[PDB]
Length: 204
Length: 204
Ligand SMILES: COc1ccc(NC(=O)Nc2ccncc2)cc1
Ligand SMILES: COc1ccc(NC(=O)Nc2ccncc2)cc1
Ligand SMILES: [Ca+2]
Ligand SMILES: [Ca+2]
Image (cartoon, rainbow over all chains, first blue to last red; front, side, top):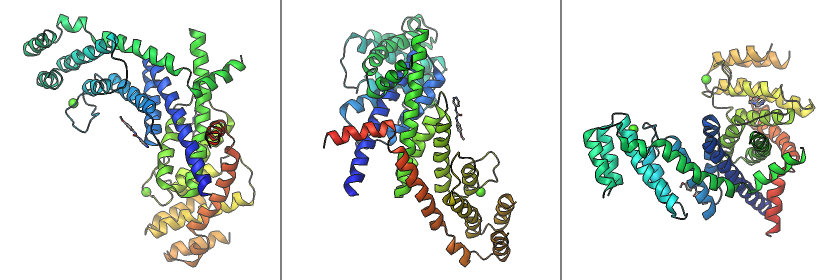
């Protein structure tokens, strides 16, 4: 009875890990497709499964960081969303912190995404008329040539500057989508998706 | 690409059905063991998975009703919880409505549970000093010999009456736990739990 409860708890922890990987895969696919409502619903399911986790491997921590990173990027223009205990941290700044924590290769795409999030963290403040907040985000991030150009834009209040059109929010989204495609290909072979695909294919 | 998206959506619907059955099984086990916090966390996960459902079979509707029924029973003494659009319906009255809707055998245990929920729906109002609400719950439910005894208790405001000690909240819980044991035995062979148990047993 005591050892049976233990085997039951271990089996629940295995099933939760399979559910976490599947929801991360579904969250990446909805992010890549731009299916906003499916992303919202899947995010809610991933948050609940994470709250119930019995144990955590290094691979599961990376999966959690990936889900949290996409959530913050999706909320990038929602300056009223508070992702940290420090109420001053904006969603794109929270995404930047997670990006610097994930155990992943720092290839050229990694740095391109990092720099696009840095520029957009300032740009989204400027677009809403939050000029003082843009300077505070800049000070927190910066903690150059690129750096001095950004401070000049903030001081001029040049919201629709050509610089933000070349290093745009859409460009940040497209570079993140390229990374998401790699995560999708990697997690497509996880247990629950493979088993579900086999059931579907067998009925075809 | 269009047919690939379709196969992907079908596979996600299969995986969601497997997750729903597993969470119902975990919810039943936590209810049976009296693990209140595990029940709360599992309930949150089941609610999120239900909100994301792509399709629904008669078996999945029964599983949803089972989860909702246990939630209402667990909230039976929380008269501030509103489970219906009509704000007047108490949690045990909401549990009674679901109990009368589930496609299940109406054996002796079914009726014993039904009658215990009816008595306790009044008893929980009386225990909180809600004498007028107890009469309103009685009118909604009733909609005898048992019936006339209850109206007499409500009019006398006899909160700690011997009748409520014989048809007690604990007795209602124990009868519901006997039904939960049957649901647990039936759902123990569902895909995700069977596959997780095999992984655990293989490492022993
Ligand atoms: C970066 O954000 C998060 C990181 C980790 C968790 N959860 C977590 O560590 N849970 C856990 C459960 C049981 N054993 C060990 C660990 C939640 C959020
Ligand atoms: C008794 O409470 C509930 C009953 C059913 C649902 N969901 C539901 O019917 N979803 C669905 C999704 C796609 N195709 C058909 C149906 C939710 C709550
Ligand atoms: Ca704000
Ligand atoms: Ca109330």
